[PDB]
Image 1 (tube, chains in turn orange, yellow):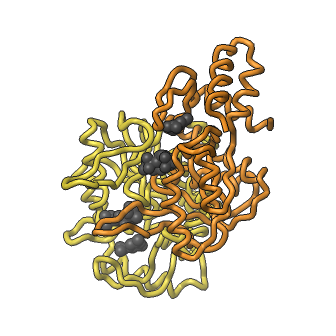
Image 2 (cartoon, rainbow over the protein chains, first blue to last red; image 1 turned 30 degrees about the vertical axis):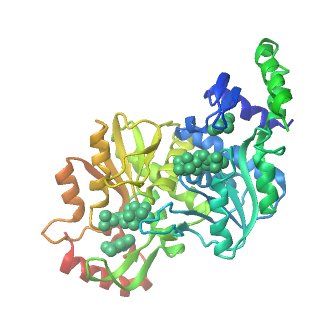
Image 3 (cartoon, rainbow over the protein chains, first blue to last red; image 1 turned 45 degrees about the vertical axis):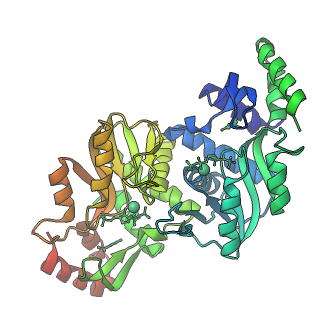
Length: 213
Length: 213
Ligand SMILES: O=P(O)(O)OC[C@H]1O[C@H](OP(=O)(O)OP(=O)(O)O)[C@H](O)[C@@H]1O
Ligand SMILES: O=P(O)(O)OC[C@H]1O[C@H](OP(=O)(O)OP(=O)(O)O)[C@H](O)[C@@H]1O
Ligand SMILES: O=C(O)c1cc(=O)[nH]c(=O)[nH]1
Ligand SMILES: O=C(O)c1cc(=O)[nH]c(=O)[nH]1
Ligand SMILES: [Mg+2]
Ligand SMILES: [Mg+2]
C-alpha cells in the first residue's frame, strides 16, 4: 500500500472521519466502521484532502481534461483538488460544477466554471448507491462531453442488491473507471499493523467475509 | 497601493477578468470597464485567487471565526480562501456554506461544513446591488451567529439609486464592514503608471467623475 494511502487513513482517523463501532448503513446493513467525509470541514482539512485527491489522480495515469464537482458535496472537493493539482503537480486544469437548481417543472442543467468539454474526471466523496452520479453523467453526456473516470475517497467493496458492488455497476453501466484513494483492503492491511486494533481488525475482517466483493 | 493589490490587477487583466471597453451594467449604466470573476475557472486561477483573498483578510486585521461562502459563487471562493489561509498563513479555520435549496413552499436554511457559530466573515466576488448577502445575513442572523465582515474582490465605489454605494448601504444596514482586494481607486492609480493605457485612464477617470462616490 502506498505512502499517501497510509497517511490518508491516519488523517481520516485523526479527524474521526473513520470510525469503528457499530453503524447502520443506508442499505440497512449493520457495519463495523463508517466513513463520513462530512467531517472534513476546516481550512486545513480542505487543504489536506485536495493533496490526497491529486496524488491519487496523478498516480492513476488516466487522461482527462477537466474536473467536475457535483451537486453540493463535490464542489469544495473539485475546487480543492484543482488547486492541489496546480500548486504541486504543476497541472493546471479547468473546473466546472452544476447548479442542482431546477426552479421550474423539469430538471436543471446550469453550470459554473469551465465548459463541459473533453474528457471529464468526476469527483466525489463516496458512492453508496451510485445513483447520484448517474444524474451527473447525464449532464456530461448531454453537453456531449465524455467521461474519463470517477474518483472517490473510499471503495467499501461490498455487494449491492446483486453480487457486484455499486461501484462495479457504475463502471459497468457507464463504461468508465472509478478510482479511489483507499479501499477496504488497505483498511485491513492497516489495521494489521496496529496491534491494539485487533478488535476492529476482526470485525472488519468478518464483515468483508459476509459481504465483501 | 500594496504589492498583492498590483499583482491582483495584473492577473485580472491577464485572465481578462478586467476589461476596458464599453459595458452596460445591470443598473443600466454604460461603464468603461468591467470585472467578471466568472472567468477565473481554472485550477491555478483558483489557487491564485485564494492567496489574494487570504492576504487581504490578513491584511485587514479583522477578527473572525469562520468563512462562509454563499449561494453558488461563494463556495469555491470560501473553499480556496480557506485552503490559502491554512497553507500560507498558518491559520486554520472552519468553513461553511448554504444550500440555495428551498425544495418546498418557503425558503432554505440547510448548510454544509462547520457550524454557523461565532464571528462570521462573509466571502463573495462582487456586490452590485448588495442584495444577495442580505439573503445571506439572514441565515447568519438566524443561527444566532454574528457578522464579522464581508470580503469581495472589487469595490467599484459608485453611487447606487441614492447617494451612497451599494456597499455603504450594506455596511450601513448590517453594521459590518466590507473589505476588498481592490478598489476603483487602485485601478486608476494603476492605469496611471501605464503610459499607453491613457485612453482607459481617461475614461475611468471621467466615469469616476460622473458617478464615483
Ligand atoms: O452514491 P449515492 O447513494 O447516490 O450517494 C453518494 C452521495 O451522498 C451524498 O449526496 P448528497 O446528494 O446528499 O450531497 P449534497 O449535499 O451535495 O447534496 C454525498 O455528497 C455523495 O455525493
Ligand atoms: O450584489 P448582487 O446584485 O446581489 O449580486 C452579486 C452576486 O451576483 C452573482 O450572484 P448569483 O446569485 O447569480 O450567483 P450564483 O451563481 O452563486 O447563484 C454573483 O455570484 C454575486 O454573488
Ligand atoms: O453505505 C453507507 O451508507 C455509507 C458508508 C460509509 O462509509 N459512508 C457513507 O457516507 N455512507
Ligand atoms: O455592476 C455590474 O453590473 C457589474 C460590474 C462589474 O464590474 N462586475 C459585475 O459582475 N457586475
Ligand atoms: Mg453529493
Ligand atoms: Mg452568488
